[PDB]
RNA sequence: CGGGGGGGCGAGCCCCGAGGGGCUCUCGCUUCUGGCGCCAAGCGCCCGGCCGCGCGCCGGCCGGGCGCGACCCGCUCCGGGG
RNA sequence: CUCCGUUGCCCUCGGCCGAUCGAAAGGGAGUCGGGUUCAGAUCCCCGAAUCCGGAGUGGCGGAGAUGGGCGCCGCGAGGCGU
């Protein structure tokens, strides 16, 4: 609906009840989740490989 | 040592005082010229206005052209110890501002016509 | 354990592109408005250029040890304030028409303030010492004065601060000052300064008169030009 | 970009210094696909974009 | 930024006692994936109140402040000419 | 002078981007049936509406929100203490 109309409407008509709800489209949130592991985890895997490279050296 | 976080210089915000004038700059305050005798000039008595009084609980007024509705309302109220539901103004081709004033239902136009002398 | 397990560390790292950078002082990386920028690079030019002797002498100045004796000495001696003036007159008006008064008294010796006052009584050899401010704005007004002072054989000196020199005499600023006479008791301290000053000034002139005083580059340039003389030394000193 | 043979590319970095996101307009080098990280500056590696 | 100075994982050289030091480099630390990243944690050092021990810069509770973190100094806001 | 408001100063935070005008056809919330005049009618009236702003003191409902545990006392519905 024509955007100024949103000021009349209730909160619940404008989102869906979630993370990134009503701005982002599920399919991209659920990748943003399981990207946000594997970025995080593989800093840990580089963190320990770096620690083992300096333990070797 | 009050370090500069930002790389702009913005002017310092100074103190700036309030007018303490040594005289008033004009002697007296101007007498108010839009009054409860001046803002209303005359009620119309046209047939399409008698017809409007009797049928619609209104009164048709010519009004001073700088008048607002809350001025016309606190005029018509002040004078014909009346009270006003709503005001509704136009400018006649002639420059005369009309304003036809609906009077609250408790209260009649056809009586307050004869008080103000029209009819 | 008086150490709740939760309070941790979260130590950030501000390498390029890592965690976002914090707030350093930037006073050199900031936009210095047009008075400042300007006044900043007057002081630079005024070292960068080859400044003349006559304008140089207005850098080399007195030191704490000498300066503070001078400004002690003057404090016996500042010209009458206003109010202090009034009771010099008012007391003579009552003393005249009561208990005798020829009314010359003896005008106690005091300072002398401005330039075209000083220079006359330097050109008259009527001065023991002359104090000159260094920072004077049109330098014109005190360029000569040292030269003039040494020709008349008058001890001159260059104190810092036209303000603190212009605070003796009760004003904002002053460019010169002078003791013509002194109180008898106070003459040992005057003649103590005089001999100390003119070893250091009047009897220097062919050291002062021919000393140009700028021609000094920026430390950024100097650091670079010197870093090439470690290249040229260590080419054929090794 | 009208009146211009090259396509542009909007490339969002982020300001290394204020929490925000600067965006720019590089002239698209050929082989700029959409979704590329583009490395910039002295220490950057030698590849396209 | 230019100098300086910390760091230090590391390389060259110099020294060395085999602990280590000096000089040189390197860094100044973010590259497999449309991921997150500000308003500061941590340590330190202090002060107000309040409570407990009572000596109270002992301890608790409540509430603040500064230092490091985030090296120090400068003289041209950075770059290119002249 | 409660608490609130208002203002004074002190500390704290804020990039912008150009003093300003430019649409009766571009961008821009919300009004429509019926009635009515000689001439006017989303304009007047009747009825149905609707937007924006205000609502402080909060006008009134409803949400926040009404458990569980433990411990007693009560047949049991249950009551109380924590
Ligand atoms: Mg406009
Ligand atoms: Mg339009």
Image: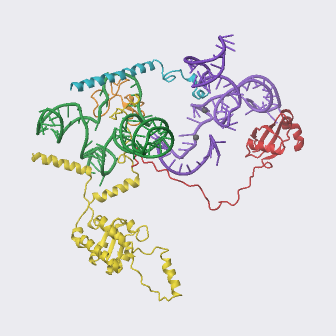
Chain colours: A cyan, B red, C yellow, D orange, E green, F purple
Q: Quadrant of the N terminus of chain C?
A: top left
Report the front residue among F64 and E61.
Answer: E61
Residue C55 vertical position relative to residue C25 in the rendered view, above or below: below
Report the front residue among F12 and D32.
Answer: F12
Label count reads 0
Q: Quadrant of the C terminus of chain C?
A: top left
Q: Is residue F46 left or right of residue F14?
A: right
Give the percent coordinates (x, y) of residue F50: 67, 27
Q: Residue at x 48, y 74 (%)?
A: C82
Give the percent coordinates (x, y) of residue E67: 36, 44
Q: Which corner quadrant of the figure contains ligand 1?
A: top right
Q: Is residue C93 left or right of residue C235?
A: right
Q: Is residue E27 left or right of residue D28?
A: left
Q: Residue at x 33, y 23 (%)?
A: A44
Q: Residue at x 37, y 55 (%)?
A: C38
Is any part of residue B119 visible from this angle?
A: no
Give the percent coordinates (x, y) of residue B8: 41, 46
Give the percent coordinates (x, y) of residue F71: 57, 18
Residue E10 vertical position relative to residue E48 in the rendered view, above or below: above
Q: Is residue F35 left or right of residue D18?
A: right
Is any part of residue B18 visible from this angle?
A: yes
Report the front residue among E71 and C117.
Answer: E71
Image quadrant assignment for residue A13: top right
Report the front residue among B108 and C172.
Answer: C172
Q: Residue at x 45, y 48 (%)?
A: B10
């Amino acid at each position: 609906v024509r955007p100024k109309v949103l000021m009349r409407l209730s909160k619940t008509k404008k989102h869906v009840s979630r993370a990134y709800g009503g701005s982002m489209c599920a399919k991209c949130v659920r990748d943003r989740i399981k990207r946000a592991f594997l970025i995080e985890e593989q800093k840990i895997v580089v963190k320990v490989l770096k620690a083992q490279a300096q333990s070797q050296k | 040592k009050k370090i500069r976080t930002s790389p702009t210089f913005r002017r310092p915000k100074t103190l700036r005082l309030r007018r303490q004038p040594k005289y008033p700059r004009k002697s007296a305050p101007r007498r108010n010229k839009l009054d409860h005798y001046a803002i209303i000039k005359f009620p119309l008595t046209t047939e399409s206005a008698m017809k409007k009084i009797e049928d619609n609980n209104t009164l048709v007024f010519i009004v001073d052209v700088k008048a607002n509705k809350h001025q016309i309302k606190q005029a018509v109220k002040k004078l014909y110890d009346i009270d006003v539901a709503k005001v509704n103004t136009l400018i006649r081709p002639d420059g005369e501002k009309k304003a036809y004033v609906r009077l609250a239902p408790d209260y009649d136009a056809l009586d307050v016509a004869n008080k103000i002398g029209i009819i | 354990k008086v150490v709740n397990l939760l309070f941790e560390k979260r130590p950030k790292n501000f390498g390029i592109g890592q965690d976002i950078q914090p707030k350093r002082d930037l006073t050199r990386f900031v936009k210095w408005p047009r008075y400042i920028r300007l006044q900043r690079q007057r002081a630079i030019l005024y070292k960068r250029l080859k400044v003349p002797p006559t304008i140089n002498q207005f850098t080399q100045a007195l030191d704490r040890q000498t300066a503070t004796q001078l400004l002690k000495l003057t404090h016996k001696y500042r010209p009458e304030t206003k109010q202090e003036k009034k009771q010099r007159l008012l007391a003579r008006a009552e003393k005249k028409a009561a208990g005798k008064g020829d009314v010359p008294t003896k005008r106690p010796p005091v300072l002398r303030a401005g330039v075209n006052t000083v220079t006359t009584l330097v050109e008259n050899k009527k001065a023991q010492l002359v104090v000159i401010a260094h920072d004077v704005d049109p330098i014109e007004l005190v360029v000569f004065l040292p030269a003039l002072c040494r020709k008349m054989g008058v001890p001159y000196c260059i104190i810092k601060g036209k303000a603190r020199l212009g605070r003796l005499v009760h004003r904002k600023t002053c460019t010169t000052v002078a003791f013509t006479q002194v109180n008898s008791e106070d003459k040992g301290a005057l003649a103590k300064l005089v001999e100390a000053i003119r070893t250091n000034y009047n009897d220097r002139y062919n050291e002062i008169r021919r000393h140009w005083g700028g021609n000094v580059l920026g430390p950024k340039s100097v650091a670079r030009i010197t870093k090439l003389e470690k290249a040229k030394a260590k080419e054929l000193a090794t | 970009d009208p009146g211009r043979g090259a396509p542009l590319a909007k490339v969002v970095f982020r300001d290394p210094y204020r929490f925000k996101k600067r965006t720019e307009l590089f002239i698209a080098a050929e082989g700029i696909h959409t979704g590329q990280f583009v490395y910039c500056g002295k220490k950057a590696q030698l590849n396209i974009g």
